[PDB]
Length: 300
Ligand SMILES: C[S@@+](CC[C@H](N)C(=O)[O-])C[C@H]1O[C@@H](n2cnc3c(N)ncnc32)[C@H](O)[C@@H]1O
Ligand SMILES: CN[C@@H]1[C@H](O)[C@H](NC)[C@@H](O)[C@H](O[C@@H]2O[C@H](C)C[C@H](O)[C@H]2O)[C@H]1O
Ligand code: SF4
Ligand code: SF4
Ligand SMILES: [Cl-]
Ligand code: NA
Image (cartoon, rainbow, N blue to C red; front, top):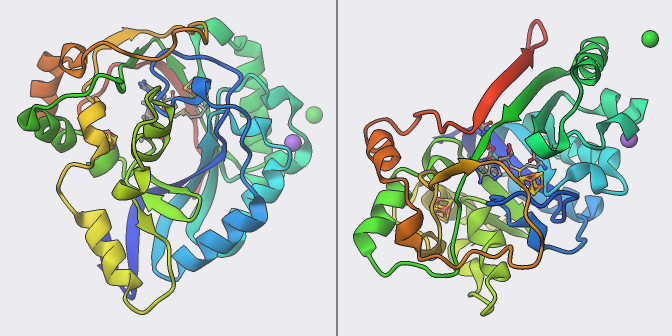
């Protein structure tokens, strides 16, 4: 992340969650979407908030995602609301693909890039993926299809009191330091989806996630506040209940809603060998994607 020409520049993306809910129930969903009921972003509200933020912030892309963004009633309108702010160079939609065959030609015209996460329990036939590749080529859309074999544990209601562990997890966290998973929610900016979406779903009520957020504002001192927030190198309140990027690997599966919540003590869920690996190289592959199909667009 850089400070240049009056704005904080993110070489990665700003994340806009169209829908907090999902039609799947993946174990260890990083946004805890299986625990959320229907909540669809207001395109006008998103446009206003990102318009304010764009005066001081620019990213390479805007990632429209959430739980499952294709559940949104007006995803093209949300896409265009994001594009109109100029906050990013391109607009990307990330989807589990289970609803992509319902999308109309305005969806394919509206997106710049499309990322489909394909999971074992909701497999898309290779011929349907080929159809998606053809549609993407036809509309000049960069396409990435990731076939997930595993997920890593992401959080627990039983957090840790060990400050060294929190520091190790935050220090190796790809979301905070590498992917720059900056997340806009309800007028606040967050370093990561976990810090805003996980506390609200802890069964004891959690805490106010705004302690880890930055209120999005226009005032002449917003830029510097933003730069300090996005460059700060101290763990968040949420890291004490988060596994970051070093959670234990497990086969990807869906679980029933009943008992979905995680209670095992956080220290038991750290993949300590992988934590060493990531301590040496923060970009180390997480082992979650088993196969990937990429169809880029020339000149992109
Ligand atoms: C919340 S999902 C994005 C929305 C969309 N429904 C999807 O899954 O593609 C965020 C991204 O992180 C991945 N993800 C979610 N939970 C994960 C976990 N526990 N470990 C590794 N990747 C995870 C998903 O595969 C997806 O690429
Ligand atoms: C291997 N799979 C990764 C990978 O493809 C990344 N490519 C840079 C991508 O950034 C990741 O996505 C982010 O994963 C976080 C857990 C949450 C965040 O909301 C989401 O954007 C995705 O999981
Ligand atoms: S498809 Fe799975 S990982 Fe993606 S939002 Fe839904 S439950 Fe979470
Ligand atoms: S809560 Fe902490 S460890 Fe978890 S994703 Fe955010 S910065 Fe990373
Ligand atoms: Cl045709
Ligand atoms: Na559509």
